[PDB]
Amino acid sequence: KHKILHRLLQD
Amino acid sequence: KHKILHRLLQD
Amino acid sequence: EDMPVERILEAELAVEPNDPVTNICQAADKQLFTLVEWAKRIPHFSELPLDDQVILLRAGWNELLIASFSHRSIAVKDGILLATGLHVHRNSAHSAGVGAIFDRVLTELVSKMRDMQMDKTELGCLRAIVLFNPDSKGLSNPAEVEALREKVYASLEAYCKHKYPEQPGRFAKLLLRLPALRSIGLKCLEHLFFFKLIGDTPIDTFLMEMLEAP
Amino acid sequence: EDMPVERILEAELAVEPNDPVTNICQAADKQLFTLVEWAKRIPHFSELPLDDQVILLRAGWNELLIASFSHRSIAVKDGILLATGLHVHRNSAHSAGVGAIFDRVLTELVSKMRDMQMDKTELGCLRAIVLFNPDSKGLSNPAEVEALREKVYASLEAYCKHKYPEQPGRFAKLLLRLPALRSIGLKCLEHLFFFKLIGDTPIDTFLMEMLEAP
Ligand SMILES: CC1=C(/C=C/C(C)=C\C=C\C(C)=C\C(=O)O)C(C)(C)CCC1
Ligand SMILES: CC1=C(/C=C/C(C)=C\C=C\C(C)=C\C(=O)O)C(C)(C)CCC1
Image 1 (tube, chains in turn blue, orange, cyan, yellow):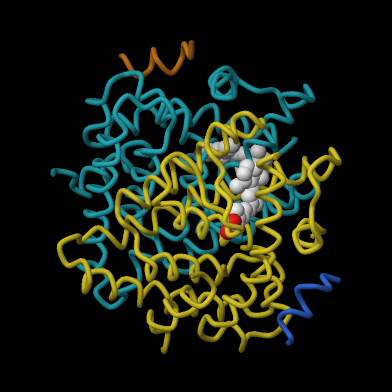
Image 2 (cartoon, chains in turn red, green, purple, brown):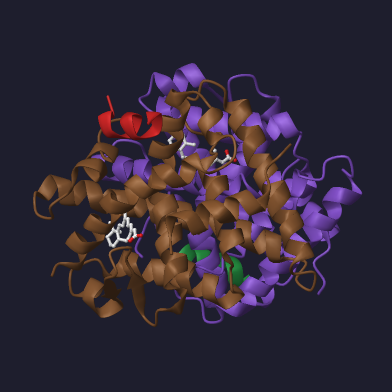
């Protein structure tokens, strides 16, 4: 869940 | 308005 | 000028030596009367105009009562001790449908007060700070209330550091429980408005008056 | 150990050089991306497990964004300046049905930040404190987050007193705007859930994700 937030934090 | 509170504060 | 923690501690010591929701609401109505007596013992509160005294108490009663039973419950295992001498266990709150907010009280307030061993003087000052809420709408002179609040936290900080020199961050730790107290207080009001709407849960006259508009 | 206000100030300076509600929601979605970049620049945040980073941001995004546009608006007369370069006047918010909450932002946050001349370092630290919210549910190690928060306010206090020696109560005054920020943030969320329910007011993907459960 929470696709955008995870992606932005990982990069 | 607020009968109880006023009465208690005045006494 | 002139806001000794000794007077604040005295105010604290002077007022305190089946549906769990009903029992809690009854304890709250009972404590609302005691809250007025407590406020009257807080330096300069009684010298503010009557309408502002009303405003401050209507704006802070729920947080003020929550802070008090939470601190009283520091000794309690998994629950809270009501002023009526009754205990409400976490399982009981859960079984009545109010488990989420009840757990927030235990987790964010009771447990934290216990972890840091918050004392009565500190609790008293934190409540006096809540009481003197300058943001309260309708205040005839908010600057005056703001000044009283500043005198309280100035005295609180001196108390800390003098009593707990080994804990430089204690003063900040105390003030940082206020946002949780604010959030919890707001959620409790929501529940109360709901209980009143639903019709179940007897609500006494003083508690009912506090739920009246504004 | 190791939470220099200099790094916090840098994070702040690194991220920032018709329906007003729609414009505000668009600015919020835009700033949510920038908020992630800001958090990554706050010491030790990126070293916390990914799931806790998510938890902290989902728990504090609204208060974090409100603190930022409020401080940015200190120069503004009767309104706020959005990151999109747009200004929302108090009269405009009122005419859109969101006057009450808008006035709370101006009164309890903007005006107060202006009155005390809160600076960017202070704002940065207050936001870092909000970010490191130990009460956030689901945290794998709340003690760790609690420790980071304590390092922030310890550094904030040193900054104050060293920069504003003449204002002994400044540190407390800063922390005491947090309960208002918490209350305002909660009310804003209520409005947002309503706008989403009603259907009017376009809501972008990141803002929408933040409104998703839990
Ligand atoms: C705590 C509680 C609620 C509200 C309590 C309130 C509003 C006051 C309690 C005062 C007490 C308990 C005073 C005392 O006993 O000294 C809500 C509505 C969340 C329901 C769950 C239990
Ligand atoms: C303020 C506002 C609302 C919410 C704003 C939120 C949730 C975020 C704003 C972020 C901004 C404005 C960022 C920026 O521009 O930097 C509510 C729902 C109360 C409606 C009234 C106007």
